[PDB]
Amino acid sequence: TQSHYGQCGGIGYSGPTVCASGTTCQVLNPYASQCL
Image (cartoon, rainbow, N blue to C red; front, side):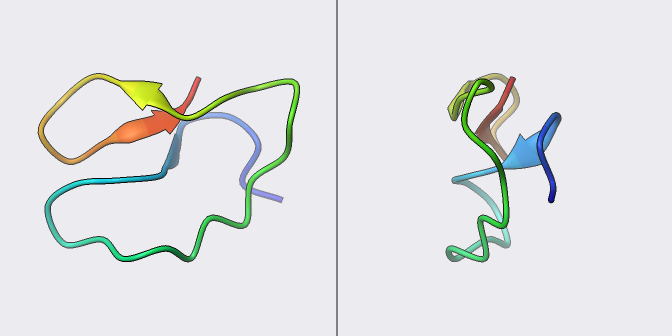
């Protein structure tokens, strides 16, 4: 599982979000709202 530092939205992406909960899906660089 791509638990931490996992891309959820931005440049080049779609939705292969094979992440866990506990971590999230929130903003940093233009590539990623991401599993922090």
